Amino acid sequence: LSTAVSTLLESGSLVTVAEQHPVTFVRNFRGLAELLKVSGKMQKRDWKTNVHVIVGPPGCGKSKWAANFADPETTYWKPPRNKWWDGYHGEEVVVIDDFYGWLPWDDLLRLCDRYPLTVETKGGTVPFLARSILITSNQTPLEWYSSTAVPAVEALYRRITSLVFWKNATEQSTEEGGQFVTL
Amino acid sequence: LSTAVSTLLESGSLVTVAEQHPVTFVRNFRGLAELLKVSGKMQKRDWKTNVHVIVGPPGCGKSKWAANFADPETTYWKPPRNKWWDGYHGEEVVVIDDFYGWLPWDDLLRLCDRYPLTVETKGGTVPFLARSILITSNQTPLEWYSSTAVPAVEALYRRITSLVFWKNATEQSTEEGGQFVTL
Amino acid sequence: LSTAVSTLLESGSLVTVAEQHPVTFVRNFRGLAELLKVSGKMQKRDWKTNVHVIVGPPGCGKSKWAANFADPETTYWKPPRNKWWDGYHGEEVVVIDDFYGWLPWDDLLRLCDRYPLTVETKGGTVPFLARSILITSNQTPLEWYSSTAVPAVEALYRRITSLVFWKNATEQSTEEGGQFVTL
Amino acid sequence: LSTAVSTLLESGSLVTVAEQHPVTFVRNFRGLAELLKVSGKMQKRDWKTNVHVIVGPPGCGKSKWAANFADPETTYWKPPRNKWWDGYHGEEVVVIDDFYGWLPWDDLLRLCDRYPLTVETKGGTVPFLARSILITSNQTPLEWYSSTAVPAVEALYRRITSLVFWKNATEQSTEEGGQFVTL
Amino acid sequence: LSTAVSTLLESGSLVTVAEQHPVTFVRNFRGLAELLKVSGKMQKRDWKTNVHVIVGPPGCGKSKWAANFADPETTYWKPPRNKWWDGYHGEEVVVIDDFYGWLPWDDLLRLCDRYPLTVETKGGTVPFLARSILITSNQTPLEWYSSTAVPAVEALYRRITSLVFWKNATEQSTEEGGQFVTL
Amino acid sequence: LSTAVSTLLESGSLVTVAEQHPVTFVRNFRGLAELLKVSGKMQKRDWKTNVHVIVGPPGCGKSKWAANFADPETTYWKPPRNKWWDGYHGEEVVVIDDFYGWLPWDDLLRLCDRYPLTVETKGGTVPFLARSILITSNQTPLEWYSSTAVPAVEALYRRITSLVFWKNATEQSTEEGGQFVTL
DNA sequence: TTTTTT
Ligand SMILES: Nc1ncnc2c1ncn2[C@@H]1O[C@H](COP(=O)(O)OP(=O)(O)O)[C@@H](O)[C@H]1O
Ligand SMILES: Nc1ncnc2c1ncn2[C@@H]1O[C@H](COP(=O)(O)OP(=O)(O)O)[C@@H](O)[C@H]1O
Ligand SMILES: Nc1ncnc2c1ncn2[C@@H]1O[C@H](COP(=O)(O)OP(=O)(O)O)[C@@H](O)[C@H]1O
Ligand SMILES: Nc1ncnc2c1ncn2[C@@H]1O[C@H](COP(=O)(O)OP(=O)(O)O)[C@@H](O)[C@H]1O
Ligand SMILES: [Mg+2]
Ligand SMILES: [Mg+2]
Ligand SMILES: [Mg+2]
Ligand SMILES: [Mg+2]
């Protein structure tokens, strides 16, 4: 356990302690996470996270493309209508699926901002090291959060990387331009 | 417990650990489960979950067909009226009984899909992997939800794999999908 | 403990362990309940919970008969009006007392079915295993729930086993479902 | 520990253990609680709880009589306008202070009844074991509740054991039977 | 921790246990809370609370004399317009600031009585043991509540131990208390 | 160990405890947190909070000026149009944006006073320690309320420190404050 | 954490 802290407080936690020291992590699993969170070494983030937004009527393979995006080993699916990010003890595809506006708008913005973040799970907090958020929906992206219920709708628009609509029941087409309020 | 951790590392199932070495699994059960979560060898889902829907007036014998279907030992009779799936911890009949829509719409769509999902318990989250869901009702699925308060109701009918009915005081005659609505 | 776990895995009931060696159940009590949940030997229900309904104006001795139906060591008196089956860790008799309709309709339909059920306790889940639900009321089962606001009022009546009624200020006489809407 | 388990399982609730071997109750406290709840010997109430109402205009030394009815070690003064019984853990005499009608009717009946009951606390449940409910009030029991919203007001008066009143005299005089409805 | 228990059962305050024993409170911090809560001996109010109503038009240092009452540290400041006494943790001075009547009339009649009470906090209840309730206001105690809405009605104007007005922009003159209804 | 408490009682911060002695912070972390939360008095406030009102015609670069008052990383941007200061931890710029009269009058008068206050989130309370409140509005502070509904009625302007205005497309001019009702 | 709380 003396060596356990030494390995823990280098980088890349807790995945590498659990890989390297399996026995000592069966015990103290709450405490290693608390020590790491207390110190300023939770592997923070400085990269603008990519946001891909998909729109199309159901049955048009919205989520199929999200599944076929990166390796399934390194993919997380946000369970909807639930503000708990349990299961994020790996990382870095995050596919919030089948959206209808069920997240607090400010937090949704915070996930799409550039600053570091720490989401909360059942039994502590976990750093949010995302690189591509595939926000998959079925409706127009504007309607998710009403303009009266939001201080500024354009703030959400600013951090979108790319957007995809659906064509006349044949093709997935990429939306390019200012058909709606652009960024 | 080093043997127990190694025999968890490759098998990746707490059920096996509890079968082999109960004593260690009794003393440190949060630790083993969290180690399994962090090491990434969890059990995601990549298969379509069949949704057999039974409809009939009460007393006709809907639920006895669910209670005899797969095995008395591998069916999880879902606790009703609430979003808690406690005690589930693996496997693969999930029988939501006596349903009339008392589950959130988006979550009911998400239970009946091919892509992964973590489901919520009193203490944390247990991954969802169901090879077949049996839904028992008194109304037809056309009126489980408000057809106006739901954006696109075709996205539920598209997931049901078989809609079994009750005919005029004779038997449970399986209906054929795609006739009255999609299936 | 090494023997206590052995008893637990094959008795299938934490009550047994709690009575044999309490001292090794005072410690490691979460562990045993989680081994029992994982191993699958947690006890389900597959029998029919025969439901007795008692009616009569107040003070006529409804509750006394309910306390004289089984040993007080086993009768679990349901807490009123608040849908929390706390204090239940089993055994046969359940006396929901002084009933007037303070339970959701589907829960009253589903307690009395023959198939497994899990009830909520205050921060957990308890499996339901009763063999007799003595409902005690001042009103006939008609006046528990309004007919219009109920999918089918005949569903509850099918599950009532016996109906004892107080008449003519002498003594309560068992009914046979003739005058009442029969079962 | 087996001494603590002796004093617990043989007879009583956690209070007796707390009074006998505190150093064995600062440790193992959650597990003694679960052993008690699973053993089944958690003290029910099988007796009749006397109900002494006190009526008098504000300032007549109403509550002085209640605080002098029994030793302050065994008086639980219920907080007002709540359904919560927090902190109770068994306190023989229960003085509902200045009670103008802020408790549900059937719940007030069940407190004054003579058969088991488990009252609710913030995040748990506690078995009711009172023996003398002193209902200090301002009006006669005929003004606590209205006959419109009540099945039958006699159903409460049947349980008021004694009834002290204040009239135009410095003494408090008991009520011999009922000039109003009989108790 | 033998000394810690004997010190806790006498002083009845966890803060004292921590200060007189840091090391053995870092471990067994939950157990000491449960031992205190179950054993009894919790410090309950058995004295009279000394109400000091401070009244005058705004800007005259109503709050200045409120915080002047020693100490600046041991003075709970009641949250405005609210029900929950959150975080109170045991003080001796309670300064309800800038009152209008927001606390229910009966709750204010009960805060100033001479008997134990249990206030509500968001997640539990905390015993209320206060020796002076500085009710800063802007009106006299006559017009805090409507003349007819109060049913008692002379039960607040009994317990007002002190009173201070503010005269014509000169100084805070202690009201003699005789002109109004007596205190 | 023992020296952890020695280094905690002379720091007042857990961060240094983790830095110098992490090995005994991986264990016992819950108890150091409770010890700090129970031995150190909650942080009150005694400092007049500056209230810089920003007013102008809509869209005049008000929000950028608001963020430019101090560091955005320690700036709140209170969720508008409700009464839940979702913690935010104490963050000592407070920018209430687009205020147009929706907080209660006395609550706003209290938020800008020299004496402690505790705003409430959902499921708890957070101490309110703000060195600056930035009320960004649309129209004059006298139109936020009418003098009929507000029986103070000029008590807010004492609390306003300064005023920032936008003249006819020149700049965000800082108000004299000497023409209108004084500051 | 869930419960409570909203
Ligand atoms: N192995 C497979 N075989 C056949 N079809 C597949 C397979 N995997 C994915 N699909 C198709 O992917 C589509 C996913 O679309 P959909 O279920 O509408 O997404 P969502 O429900 O998230 O909007 C389905 O129409 C399904 O037919
Ligand atoms: N002991 C028995 N004897 C005869 N029939 C029975 C018995 N137990 C159950 N049944 C039948 O089994 C069927 C299924 O029971 P149940 O699942 O409670 O009804 P439902 O199908 O309406 O949910 C009912 O139609 C009932 O008549
Ligand atoms: N041990 C006993 N000895 C004598 N009489 C008893 C005993 N237990 C109960 N009783 C009688 O039984 C009756 C039960 O009353 P109660 O439970 O209020 O009826 P209900 O709950 O049906 O209205 C009481 O009136 C009481 O006189
Ligand atoms: N410990 C005590 N010492 C002195 N007097 C007391 C004590 N306890 C109660 N009293 C007296 O009892 C009376 C109780 O009055 P109060 O509680 O206001 O009315 P009620 O009891 O009708 O609510 C007071 O006038 C007080 O003088
Ligand atoms: Mg979808
Ligand atoms: Mg059924
Ligand atoms: Mg009864
Ligand atoms: Mg009183």
Image (cartoon, coloured by chain):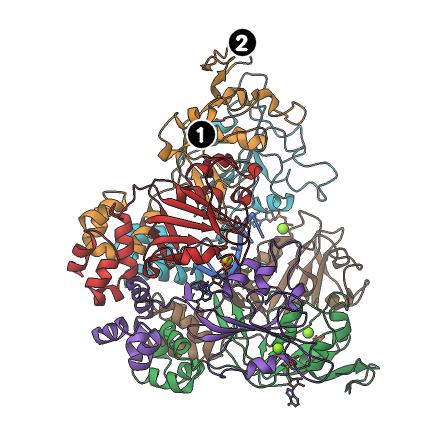
Chain colours: A red, B purple, C green, D brown, E cyan, F orange, G blue
> Residue C94: which quarter of the image?
bottom right
Q: Residue D79 location, x and y as percent? A: 57, 54
Compared with C152, D103 (above or below) is above
Question: What number is the disc on residue F179?
Answer: 2
Q: Chain of mark 2?
A: F
> Residue B171: which quarter of the image?
bottom right
Residue at 29% in and 65% down? B35
Local packing at callout 2 (Cα closer than 10 Å; few below 14, some 14-19, many 20+) is few
Quarter of the picture containing the C terminus of chain C is bottom right
- Single out the residue that lies furthest toward the top: F179
Compared with A53, E24 (above or below) is below
| Helix, strand or loop at mark 2 | loop
> Position of B4 compared to E80: left or right?
left
Residue at 25% in and 45% down? A40
Judge whether residue D69 can be spotted in this image: no
Q: Chain of mark 1?
A: E
